[PDB]
View 1: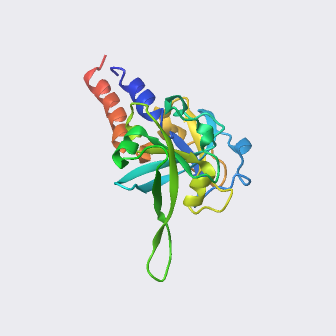
View 2 (view 1 turned 30 degrees about the vertical axis):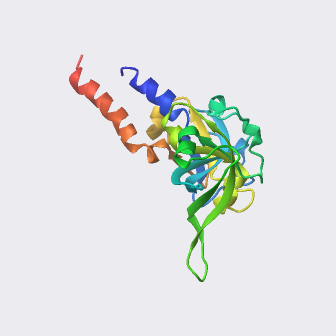
View 3 (view 1 turned 30 degrees about the horizontal axis):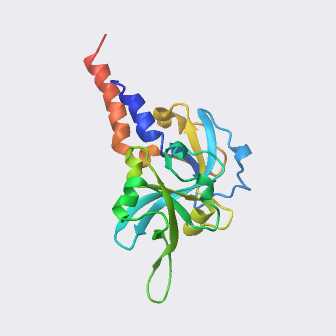
Length: 226
């Protein structure tokens, strides 16, 4: 690689979940499967996460995002890129949100504004048709990492995220993994997993990027026989 793999890993895969150990169906109960029980190879850090695709509406515009619900007390890879805002302000029940700076710009919002956050996946039935699980969140700041995630990721309190996802209280999406070697997810996904758990990874969202990694090695293989 021309630094290709290193750049992909530091600038794309650094700032998004590389993999998540979730439950087979629906949400995960961390009393059933606690952090202590996450015993896995090739993993150097684990953290709880609640994540999903969201639709955002401000006073002026609409946008798509990826909600990262985190334990505010634990450092996230985005923590160094926070712009004049502390992650610990994502207190549970406050429905605060730190937006990627470009996502904030698309929405025309600044800290002190509210945005409506919808999870159409988690819609509730009514006699008048299905409505998205939704709630207003309070913008408290931004992050600026100069990465694509600036345009769509947002950080919220994990419990607030779980509520929006309509999970049972105390449940989470699963355990976010940081991998020694994130380009090896295909092999890592084959390892022994806790019963009832399922592996997912960054290929779900960045399929063509993973294909590029594979095909660029194939190219090396084919064009440099030596």
